[PDB]
Length: 48
Length: 56
Image (cartoon, rainbow over all chains, first blue to last red; front, top):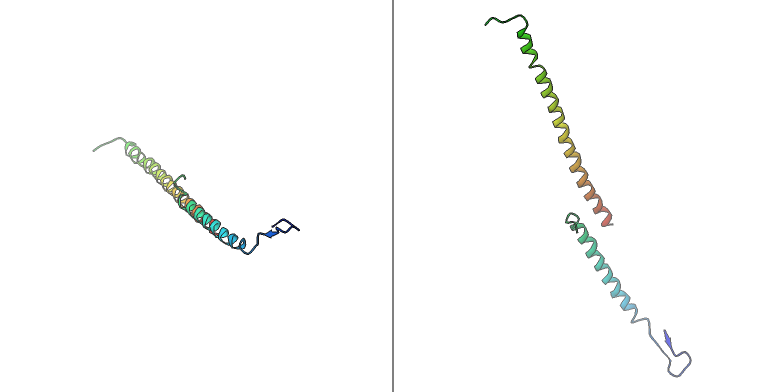
């Protein structure tokens, strides 16, 4: 994303440090689904 | 011990009906213990089934 196309004050939020966030974000979504599928099999007879 | 001419056959017949009827009660008992076999099987099969979906 480019703030200030054409002007002396032109800067750009780069992708190299955003690609690292998407890496941690994937992980924290898999961990939070494994811990949901698991815990719903275990409590199948405990009427939630 | 003297008795009339038909009494000994009334007494043998009143224990043929009893053994036949007590024979039917047995047949039906065994059937109802087969229902609790089908039921248990079903339950444990639905559990083993869900496992295979979720782990996939």
